[PDB]
Amino acid sequence: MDDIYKAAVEQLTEEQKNEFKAAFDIFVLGAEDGCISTKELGKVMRMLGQNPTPEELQEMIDEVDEDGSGTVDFDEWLVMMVRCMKDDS
Amino acid sequence: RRVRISADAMMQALLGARAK
Ligand SMILES: [Ca+2]
Image 1 (tube, rainbow over the protein chains, first blue to last red):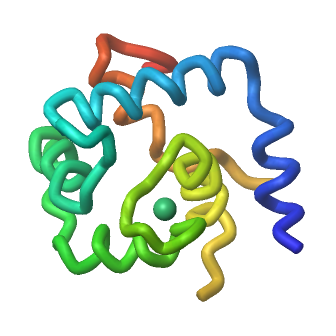
Image 2 (image 1 turned 60 degrees about the vertical axis):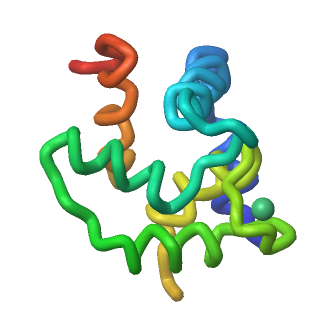
C-alpha cells in the first residue's frame, strides 16, 4: 500500500524515466556485474563534496530491496527516491 | 506540498541535467 511510490512514479516525466537509465549506467560504469554497491554509490558522494558513512548506504540498499539480493535495480531506484521523501521507518 | 529531494546533484554529474 505504497501509494506515495505509485503516484510518485506516475507524476514523473519522459525526461525523468529517460534520465533514470543514465544515472544507473554512470554509477555502474566500472561495475562488471552491473549493480550499484553501497561502496560505489558512496564513491560518488565523496567526489560530490560530501562524505556519507558506509553504514547508511549499506542499510539503505537493504531497506530498499525488492528480493533482498543486496543490489539496487532500475526499479528499486525509482522507489528509493520517494522512500526518502516519505521516510518514516 | 513539498519540494523534491536533492537528486539533481547526481543529474549534474553527466554534465548538468536540471541544474537550475
Ligand atoms: Ca534487489
